[PDB]
Image 1 (spheres, protein in one colour):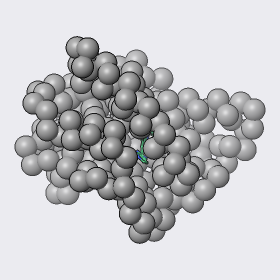
Image 2 (cartoon, helix red, strand yellow; image 1 turned 120 degrees about the vertical axis):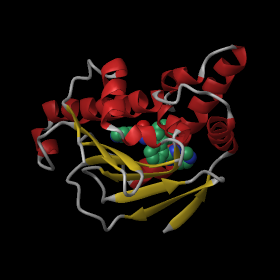
Image 3 (tube, protein in one colour; image 1 turned 90 degrees about the vertical axis):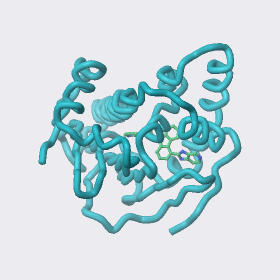
Image 4 (cartoon, helix red, strand yellow; image 1 turned 90 degrees about the horizontal axis):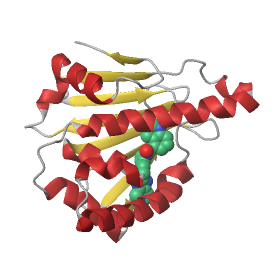
Length: 207
Ligand SMILES: O=C(NC1=c2ccccc2=C2C1=CC=CC2c1nc2ccncc2[nH]1)c1cccc2ncccc12
């Protein structure tokens, strides 16, 4: 396990999301589903030039998996996935530029719900999660786990968990007062409100 420091801008955005009073927390789910949809569109498009890119799995889907015992909500997709360089380097560049644009937009009067327009919608996970774990597998690299509970650092390690084929799992270790996002009726309500037209099957698992 390697430990990395967040740069100042993204660290400030994580604190803003964790500390600001903002009741409309449900938008995190739309943001993560949108990220999954974009990752699925990317692998699908690449497969039109190179069909062997789906040798790691033909199915293009999104699964929502609540676990009351573990207090986790997992968003699983079979999209393009992320390489180690994406996790450490490329996405750090996006986090910095997207945060700067978002903070500029907020100071003007924009809302936290607009975070996805700045490419950093993933960070809306911190509206509901104390810790976020990303398990990912890209065709050009091995399976990795990125993780952060904020506090200025994140970790990356090769993941020895169940092999994924290709894609990403965003595991939300929910805050104690955010367990409504484990309830079937609540998740169904949010998906119907914000994600009804996503171009991939979204399966809401139950317990
Ligand atoms: O939105 C996506 N992911 C991510 C973010 C989106 C924007 C910025 C940083 C993102 C990161 C995401 C996942 C894991 C780490 C990460 C990150 N690395 C960093 C290094 C240094 N500083 C800050 C950092 N933030 C995403 C990307 C590609 C395929 C996907 N598939 C499904 C769901 C999400 C994705």
